[PDB]
Length: 124
Image (cartoon, rainbow, N blue to C red; front, side, top):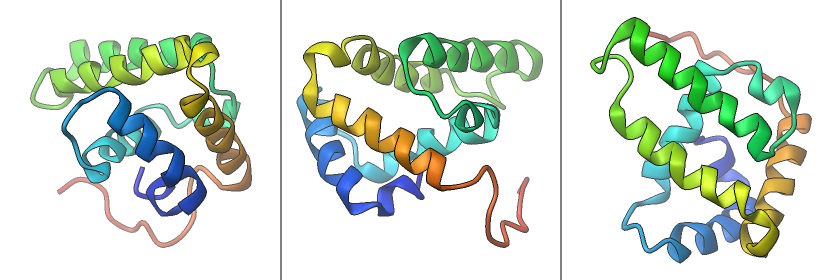
């Protein structure tokens, strides 16, 4: 999430995507959930493929994790945020603003790693 928020070319396309839905959120607020998919689905960037057929599994994952660890561990808003990206990818075919961002995210996923740098802190 905060990783993608630093890639300027992707940020330009996301400025269109955040705005076009009319949802009043900051980039920090959106990309917070992009961090959440990496932490819950470490295999998603390994597939390096961003299509709704792949993205549906991310929500299935949040649902499994939600039933196992409760709403205090996974928020119900994670599904709400997830739904926003779900419609964006499902209809990327008529949304070139996000389609370019889908391609850019795949490029960045393939260029990056599941883990890099001293992320020596998990839990709280």
